[PDB]
Length: 130
Image (cartoon, rainbow, N blue to C red; front, side, top):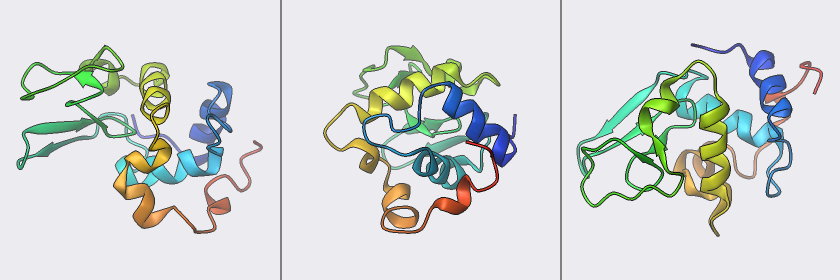
């Protein structure tokens, strides 16, 4: 499913993402926008290390979810990567929360540093009623 901007914003708020570990809703919106374009079925294979990024937040199979075919993998979140391709983003949100519980925080995603950090991200939630 491809979410509309405000629809996603409200959903993330309801799920308790606003200010989670110091991360504003506008930042989670900026991350989803650049990682998947707000698309829950987005998948990206990394030929270099044989891992795959799954879902709206492009969560990596080496440390956060299990897909069985990723070398030297771990499952911190303990989820099947299949759960991150659902239309219901409850599991993807639970996984994203786990990722930021680590010292890097939101910085775990390089895409966040390139296009979100130190920028005006208000545009991502403006007019949504959150």
